[PDB]
Length: 393
Ligand code: HEM
Ligand SMILES: O=C(O)c1ccc(OC(F)(F)F)cc1
Ligand SMILES: [Cl-]
Image (cartoon, rainbow, N blue to C red; front, side, top):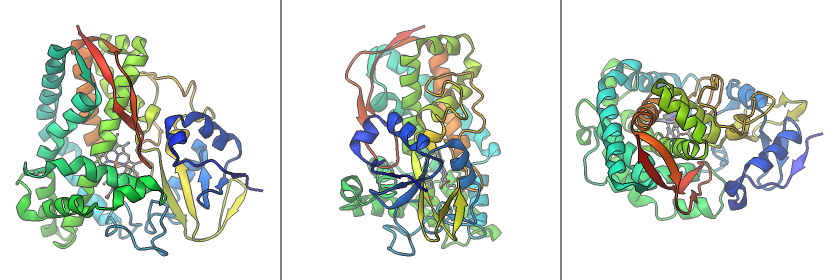
């Protein structure tokens, strides 16, 4: 009753062009079985959303990668928030919610905005730049590590560690094994920076430690919570901004609309997040036998959610393949949905908004003028290189 498919959603051919296979996954039925990895798959918006919002049945404490923590050892001590279910998840969620709070955004907005403006003006003096290295990557590295309160030494491990984290959610394919093997230097750097003495007062990391005084988290929990902010946030945001610039270069009509009303910057980034969904997939594990789309799924089964496919499901979105900076994006699952919905979403939108605002006000055209190269990762979608010529307004 459940269609079996041989599609490998973690293969390079799939990464290279996922969208046709995603329609195959969507149209085969509301629930499919992927024989290549022995997991269930849900690629329609309705089922992905239902699964995200049913945490008692589709749990997170057995890992959000392919690996089942009841069966294998996690490659690193499990995240206190991402890999936890309620009630264990609740208090670490509240701490991160407050550290990255709306109130917190007021303290960093002016510096984040200034850095984005300065970066666009800088790139306009060069003309022909790589919108990944020189923009999508450079901008977040120039604001976030400082906002964390990270010291200067060792920041070179930040991008390798982020890519490792997301590759590790995948199956035990080449990408994951190459990532995990010899990863200890990245792990050692990150773990060391999680200790209180290494975090500048006033920053996100130090503020997490400050919450150990309140009883929401204990001192031995703080380093693992700090680790969360050195795991998530960087690569996704980089890929998100990179996708936006690519979209603004492939849809010149939308760059012109954004130029005419820079206040669309925030929604132009949200639409970028739906359109490319930097986080393409992750897993839940059934805690009990469950019915989903007429399919009975046993207990202890891994379930693969296709966030990107759900964000392009024509059952939910009109013209899902088009970049529309005035689309009503409310409801997209690019940040997840429910109890685990991205706690860092306010930082990501700030970074994305102020960068697109900088572009909206200072750039007149964005033209691809060189080979575009995709960045490959088990869970993340994004570009490796995007050579563009920027025309000043
Ligand atoms: C475009 C950028 C981003 C995207 C697409 C994204 C995506 C996601 C998704 C899909 C989830 C849900 C995971 C799940 O349900 O299992 C999530 C949660 C999370 N995100 Fe983000 N994220 C982004 C930016 C950030 C930033 C900037 C931070 C930190 C500053 C961050 C930190 C986290 C954390 C700690 C969680 C775990 C939340 C929980 O388990 O309650 N992310 N993110
Ligand atoms: O707590 C962590 O280490 C963590 C890691 C990754 C992450 O991003 C996503 F996988 F998309 F949810 C969120 C949190
Ligand atoms: Cl680590």
